[PDB]
Amino acid sequence: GKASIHDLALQKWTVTNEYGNITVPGKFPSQAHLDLHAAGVIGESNNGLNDFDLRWIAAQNWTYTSKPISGLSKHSDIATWLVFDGLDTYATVKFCDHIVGTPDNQFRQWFYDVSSALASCKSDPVLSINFGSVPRIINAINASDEVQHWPASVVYPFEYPNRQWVRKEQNDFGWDWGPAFSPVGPWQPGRIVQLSKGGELYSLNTDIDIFRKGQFNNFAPDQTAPWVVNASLDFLGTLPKHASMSVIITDASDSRSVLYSGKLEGVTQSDMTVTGSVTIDAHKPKLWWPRDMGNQQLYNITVSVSSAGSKTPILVSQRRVGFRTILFSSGNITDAQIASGITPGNNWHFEINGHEFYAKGANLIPPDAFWPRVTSDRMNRLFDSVESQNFNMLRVWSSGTYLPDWIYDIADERGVLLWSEFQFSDTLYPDSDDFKANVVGEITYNVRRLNHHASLACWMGGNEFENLMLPIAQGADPATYPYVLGQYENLFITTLFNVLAANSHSISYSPCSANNGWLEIDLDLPVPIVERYYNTTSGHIYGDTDFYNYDTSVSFDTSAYPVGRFANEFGFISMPSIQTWQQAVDPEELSFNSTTVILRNHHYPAGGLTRNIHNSTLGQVEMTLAVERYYPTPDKTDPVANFSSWCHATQLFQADMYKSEIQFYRRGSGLPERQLGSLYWQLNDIWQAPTWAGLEYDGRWKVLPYVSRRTYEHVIASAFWNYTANELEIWVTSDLWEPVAGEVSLTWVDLKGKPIANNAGMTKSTKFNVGAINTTQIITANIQSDLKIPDTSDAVLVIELTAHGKLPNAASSKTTTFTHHNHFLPVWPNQAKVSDPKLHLSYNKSTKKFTVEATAGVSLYTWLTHPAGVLGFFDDNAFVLRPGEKKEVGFTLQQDTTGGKWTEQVTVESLWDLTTP
Ligand SMILES: *[C@@H]1O[C@H](CO)[C@@H](O[C@@H]2O[C@H](CO)[C@@H](O[C@@H]3O[C@H](CO[C@H]4O[C@H](CO[C@H]5O[C@H](CO)[C@@H](O)[C@H](O)[C@@H]5O[C@H]5O[C@H](CO)[C@@H](O)[C@H](O)[C@@H]5O)[C@@H](O)[C@H](O[C@H]5O[C@H](CO)[C@@H](O)[C@H](O)[C@@H]5O[C@H]5O[C@H](CO)[C@@H](O)[C@H](O)[C@@H]5O)[C@@H]4O)[C@@H](O)[C@H](O[C@@H]4O[C@H](CO)[C@@H](O)[C@H](O)[C@@H]4O[C@H]4O[C@H](CO)[C@@H](O)[C@H](O)[C@@H]4O[C@H]4O[C@H](CO)[C@@H](O)[C@H](O)[C@@H]4O)[C@@H]3O)[C@H](O)[C@H]2NC(C)=O)[C@H](O)[C@H]1NC(C)=O
Ligand SMILES: *[C@@H]1O[C@H](CO)[C@@H](O[C@@H]2O[C@H](CO)[C@@H](O[C@H]3O[C@H](CO[C@H]4O[C@H](CO[C@H]5O[C@H](CO)[C@@H](O)[C@H](O)[C@@H]5O[C@H]5O[C@H](CO)[C@@H](O)[C@H](O)[C@@H]5O)[C@@H](O)[C@H](O)[C@@H]4O)[C@@H](O)[C@H](O[C@H]4O[C@H](CO)[C@@H](O)[C@H](O)[C@@H]4O[C@H]4O[C@H](CO)[C@@H](O)[C@H](O)[C@@H]4O)[C@@H]3O)[C@H](O)[C@H]2NC(C)=O)[C@H](O)[C@H]1NC(C)=O
Ligand SMILES: *[C@@H]1O[C@H](CO)[C@@H](O[C@@H]2O[C@H](CO)[C@@H](O[C@H]3O[C@H](CO)[C@@H](O)[C@H](O)[C@@H]3O)[C@H](O)[C@H]2NC(C)=O)[C@H](O)[C@H]1NC(C)=O
Ligand SMILES: *[C@@H]1O[C@H](CO)[C@@H](O[C@@H]2O[C@H](CO)[C@@H](O)[C@H](O)[C@H]2NC(C)=O)[C@H](O)[C@H]1NC(C)=O
Ligand SMILES: *[C@@H]1O[C@H](CO)[C@@H](O)[C@H](O)[C@H]1NC(C)=O
Ligand SMILES: *[C@@H]1O[C@H](CO)[C@@H](O)[C@H](O)[C@H]1NC(C)=O
Ligand SMILES: *[C@@H]1O[C@H](CO)[C@@H](O)[C@H](O)[C@H]1NC(C)=O
Ligand SMILES: *[C@@H]1O[C@H](CO)[C@@H](O)[C@H](O)[C@H]1NC(C)=O
Ligand SMILES: *[C@@H]1O[C@H](CO)[C@@H](O)[C@H](O)[C@H]1NC(C)=O
Ligand code: NA
Ligand code: NA
């Protein structure tokens, strides 16, 4: 009595428009834009001015129609189910010309019993799904006087308005880094399931919750307590009474190694769910740790459900899990912490297996406007870049969508923690019973689906509420504010925290991405999480920092930087490379201020459907002023080269700025705020455009990820310049869990490479001692009073740190050697009297290393550019080169279309090359 499964991917599909004039072959999973493009009806969607040009697609319905489905049993003894892991978004599901469902959530798994429609069918059944025009449907919802309305500033759009009414990826209606395609279709896998009476069941969703005995969300668990493995299985259809549950927990690496094999206790069952648990000895399982914190130990758990009077199990579910505790700490700073020197207020940090760690990473946004075309290769390449940059965490930004299982699998294997969020962003949402019920379905499904993942670090209700949107609402409408605040608590706390707490004991919660923490957490309270909000005391520090300041005059002034617990967002836009631009924009539009380049810059957004040149120009100006203030301004005779050099110059500013911020946040770990995290805005691009991204759409590295890789190293030497006071401070910051000792080399040379007399009055070398997740000031000097630099515009301090220590949880007796390369320029980069360094580049086919040598003098911001046709990244880039120093640079080759020829096409340049004709 096995379950008969037909994958909908293996069925023949046809896509039709609303007006019956367009008919193209379809795919499953897919979206209309992709099927239209594959057929040649439209060009690539990311190209030119297609954000405007392709609006006729989103403005209409698209229907996915299968050819008649063969192989289904017509025996009335058999329940036939349509199972959809994702439909985007408003759809009408027809089976044999009968409407059986009307889904309205992208983030929910939909299942419909089609047994009667099948029985009624005169011939083989046709499955059709008619996807509505989301902007039309939302406009119609808003048009009703009977629904809720908010002030203009609260529901202000990026491109399409009324997005708060739909349970669809919010950036699909446009964002300030992306287009507004509003795609529709079967965005995730789908199946037809035929179940026989008294036979095998079908697994819909499985929730595995591995926690320490007595563990509760947002509270530090007991690390000496035994492990509890709770298995809750959602299914179709009929499970008989007195159900039995057994598990086999084997090592994910070796099947032969069995952790636990036995029955589950405290079995509970309902119409479509069966739950049980097992307690395992605290000493037995090997712990999972994030990357560079130990091993990423995983286990394969297979849960078998048997019925009384059945030899074989009727339901079997498998998941890959990890034994670990992850705490998001947002409660009050304890008396013990105050006594240790920590400023009072509230926490904002993470703890892995009871250990505090410094979080390093960025914000992950969707890599494509069309989720179906995002492949395993594309995500694995992105993850290579994440690891190479020395990340331990990504913030999975809302909204955004809930990532599929396969993406979390990558993070589980690699050891990258994923700070996760519910799909609510930069606006206020309705709180009607129907909307809330739809949200509950989405939260229940995704929390249950994702709980087993070792990489899941936390759940946050939404993006930018208490720090932005709620204060906007209080200003925009003081009278309606308490009501609106009440809805926020009702949806994001009362409902959402309860749905999470019911389905997870292991994952911590925060009602939004940025807040001042909580006063109380108690499920007995009408509002379970009592938020601190603006109940603050002067001098006290609360929450994470979400900081952007576009005034370029203070970009490198640390007194302008926020003093907080954690930095979850920070950034400035930069142009992508010319190679990236060439993929989407016409050659004649390859100029800094071309109409197509401007219109693709969504900083600042249109605030509607207009071609807003004014708002977009604001971002273009910000980039221009940033270059003009600090970097050599290109003036190349070749317009192509001029555009490329200006693009590069914007990247230099972005990189250096983030570095200035990262080193400041990291140094805070040893200061009274006890800063424990840096997540820059943003990691990746959704398309070819000027954004806050470090990784371009195809994966190409900007200057930013090379500078952030170094700045995210375990032990770093950071130069802090108070330019108004003319004071230089060099600090050593370590994120290791043990103290380390080491030395920092300090070499003052002129721009020709010749040493400055008496090393400009500064010591040539200094020893250091830095504590666990702490900082130490190694140098303090006034550039005028304490130092003797003959010409500040003909001087550079080269910083080289060496330290010896151990990474957390290293078995090895052998100590790791930590090295960090940095520099200090006593003037802005545009003031440095650089001369042609006369760079020589060569590639060695055996060692797979590029040799870079500066021949005539000092080279600043030495830059290697890989051509198009190759994917990957260099082992270092944007570095200082002293003459005669032969630098070896390797390349992580991810993909090559050149047959090895790409190495001949690699170019080298420096700060000097910006100002040549
Ligand atoms: C393992 O794991 C698991 C999980 O997984 C777990 O379990 C869990 O538990 C928890 C705790 O308890 C819970 O929670 C709860 O809930 C409730 C509701 O319930 C209902 O529902 C649910 C859900 O459903 C869904 O889902 C599922 C899954 O999937 C399925 O199955 C179904 O079918 C459904 O589905 C659907 O829907 C969805 C959405 O939602 C979607 O998605 C889908 O698709 C579809 O459509 C369920 O589950 C339940 O079921 C249940 O129950 C029944 C009877 O009723 C049975 O039959 C079954 O079996 C179950 O049972 C279970 O549970 C219970 C409890 O409930 C117990 O007893 C038993 O034994 C068993 O176990 C149902 O149906 C809600 O309501 C609640 O509430 C709350 O509570 C809290 C605490 O707890 C608090 O805080 C809050 O507040 C609330 O309360 C309130 O209210 C009440 C009334 O209503 C009262 O009484 C109280 O007092 C309060 O009030 C008060 O206060 C306030 C303030 O605060 C004021 O205002 C007033 O005035 C007054 O004064 C809760 O949340 C859950 O449920 C569970 N789950 C399960 C699945 O099971 C376990 O535990 C673990 N284990 C270990 C060892 O750890
Ligand atoms: C483009 O695509 C869209 C989306 O796929 C198409 O619209 C969809 O059309 C289908 C078929 O017409 C609708 O299916 C249902 O239709 C009626 C209900 O009609 C009533 O409700 C709808 C929806 O109202 C909601 O949306 C509008 C915005 O458009 C909004 O103004 C309104 O306030 C409502 O919004 C609330 O609710 C939704 C959730 O539904 C939330 O998302 C919102 O947030 C908000 O809370 C109105 O448009 C109508 O004017 C009318 O008021 C219903 O009777 C149908 O019932 C059949 O199907 C169910 C199974 O689903 C079954 O149980 C029933 O027994 C019944 O089945 C029998 O009848 C059918 C024939 O009808 C037969 O084949 C069967 O064999 C059975 O004998 C059905 O549920 C769907 O609601 C609608 N979706 C939306 C979002 O509008 C649109 O047609 C298409 N256009 C073109 C040109 O192709
Ligand atoms: C691309 O787009 C802009 C086209 O209008 C252009 O912006 C202009 O940039 C100049 C500087 O190059 C600004 O000039 C002033 O900028 C500040 C602002 O107060 C002053 O401190 C300066 O001394 C200078 O007077 C203009 O204000 C600015 N125009 C606007 C409308 O803001 C960009 O320069 C163009 N970019 C490139 C690379 O060509
Ligand atoms: C390279 O690009 C820069 C920046 O766009 C060009 O500089 C502009 O030149 C025009 C000449 O009419 C001036 O009116 C603008 O004020 C200049 N803008 C800036 C930001 O300096 C430069 O002309 C280009 N070089 C070429 C093609 O020779
Ligand atoms: C399809 O028909 C509509 C009118 O029913 C028209 O506006 C649209 O341009 C037509 N499209 C094509 C590709 O023929
Ligand atoms: C939403 O509805 C109100 C009232 O019907 C209307 O004034 C407003 O223009 C609508 N908003 C949009 C963006 O369509
Ligand atoms: C463990 O399960 C994963 C899927 O979650 C699978 O890819 C892997 O092959 C399994 N390994 C073993 C040893 O069972
Ligand atoms: C964007 O454009 C709208 C419409 O012209 C305008 O009201 C808004 O202020 C602009 N945004 C910014 C940041 O200037
Ligand atoms: C950092 O190190 C200093 C000594 O340099 C020490 O007094 C302080 O308590 C340390 N802070 C932490 C959080 O370890
Ligand atoms: Na105080
Ligand atoms: Na944001």
Image (cartoon, grey):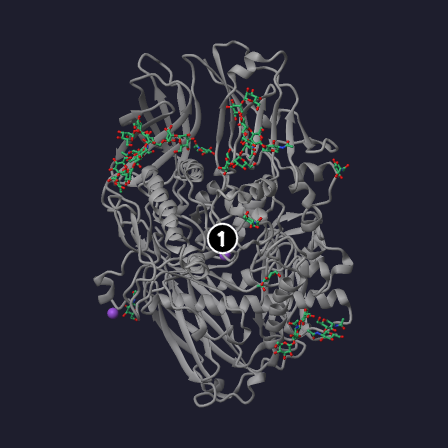
Residue 744 visible here: yes
Residue 124 position by quadrant: top right
Q: From the image, which quarter does the N terminus lie in?
A: top left
Residue at left 31%, top 14%?
308
Ligand 7 - quadrant of the structure image? top left
The answer to whether residue 860 is seen in the rendering is no
Q: In the shown orientation, is residue 275 left or right of residue 618?
A: left
Q: Position of residue 77 (x, y in %)?
A: 47, 10
- Mark 1 lies on a secondary structure that is helix
Q: Is residue 812 left or right of residue 190?
A: left
Q: Position of residue 359 (x, y in %)?
A: 40, 57
Depth check, front residue: 885 or 674: 674
When the figure is inspected, residue 725 is found, relative to residue 591, above or below; the finding is below
Q: Nearer the viewer, residue 21 or 420?
A: 21
Closer to the camera in the image, 851 or 787: 787
Q: Where 173 falls versus 736 (above or below)?
A: above
* Quarter residue 16 falls in: top right
Q: Where is mark 1, residue-wise?
A: 387
Return the x and y of residue 80 as percentages of the image width and height: 51, 18
Q: State yes or no: Cβ of the residue under disc 1 lies below 8 Å from any atom of ligand 7.
A: no
- Residue at 49% in and 53% down: 387
Q: Amino acid at mark 1?
A: Glu
Q: Is residue 467 above or below residue 109?
A: below
Tell me the quarter of the image containing the C terminus: bottom right
Q: Residues within 10 Å of mark 1 (few under 14, many from 20)?
A: some
583 sits left or right of 319 in the view: right
Give the mark count. 1
> Residue drawn 47% across and 83% down?
724
